[PDB]
Image (cartoon, helix red, strand yellow):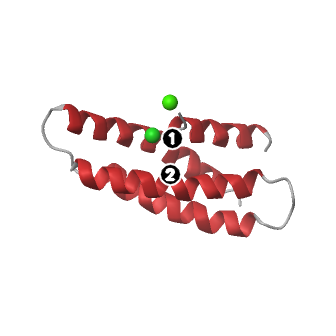
């Protein structure tokens, strides 16, 4: 069940590639 | 109150989701599109988190739980937007 915490994890994954 | 939280929550979720999809797509040249969707999502998050929810009870508690998840996401979204 995708919720905002799952979207926040997607931001974290983008940040690790910065 | 709870009804308004639910509307902002759903709209924010959709705007942030499309922004993330574009931002995650390794192809180049589309960050400008992601930026605009992030701005739309951030606006919905800010309004939704600030909705006043009064009193106790299950629906109030559920709304506040959505607001807490929105708040975590808002911090992340603003942090991403500054880099684009
Ligand atoms: Ca979850
Ligand atoms: Cl959520």
Q: Which residue is mark 1?
A: A4
Query: With respect to residue B24, does B32 lie above or below?
Result: below
Q: Which percent across, then down, holds residue B61?
A: 25, 33
**Residue B13: mark in rendering:** 2
Q: Chain of mark 2?
A: B
Q: Residue at x 80, y 54 (%)?
A: B25
Q: Which SS class for mark 1?
A: helix
Q: Residues within 10 Å of mark 1 (few under 14, many from 20)?
A: many
Q: Disc 1, disc 2: CB below 8 Å?
A: yes
Q: Which percent across, then down, holds residue B46?
A: 40, 56
- Mark 2 and ligand 2: say if the CB distance to the nearest ligand atom is below 8 Å: yes
Q: Nearer the viewer, residue B75 or B10?
A: B10
Q: Nearer the viewer, residue B7 or B54?
A: B7
Q: Residue at x 65, y 65 (%)?
A: B35
Query: With respect to residue B37, does B54 lie above or below?
Result: above
Q: Are marks 1 and 2 on the same chain?
A: no
Q: Residue at x 57, y 54 (%)?
A: B16
Q: Residue furthest front?
A: A1
| Left or right of B74 in this view: B37 | right
Q: Residues within 10 Å of mark 2 (few under 14, many from 20)?
A: many
- Mark 1 and ligand 2: say if the CB distance to the nearest ligand atom is below 8 Å: yes
Q: Residue furthest left?
A: B55
Q: Residue at x 40, y 51 (%)?
A: B9
Q: Ligand 2: which quarter?
A: top left
Alpha carbons under labels 1 and 2: distance apart: 7 Å
Q: Which percent across, then down, holds residue B10?
A: 43, 53
**Residue B64: mark in rendering:** none
Q: Which SS class for mark 2?
A: helix
Q: Which percent across, then down, holds residue B68?
A: 39, 37
Image quarter in which the C terminus of chain B is found: bottom right
Q: Chain of mark 1?
A: A
Q: Quadrant of residue B7?
A: bottom left
């Amino acid at each position: 069940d995708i919720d905002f915490d799952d979207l926040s994890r997607r931001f974290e994954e983008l940040k690790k590639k910065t | 109150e709870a009804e308004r939280v639910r509307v902002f929550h759903k709209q924010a979720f959709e705007y942030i989701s499309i922004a993330l999809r574009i931002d995650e797509d390794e192809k180049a040249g589309q960050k400008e599109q992601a930026v605009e969707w992030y701005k739309k999502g951030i606006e919905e998050l800010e309004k939704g988190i600030a909705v006043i929810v009064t009193g106790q009870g299950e629906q109030c508690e559920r709304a506040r739980r959505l607001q807490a998840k929105m708040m975590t996401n808002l911090v992340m979204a603003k942090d991403r937007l500054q880099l684009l």
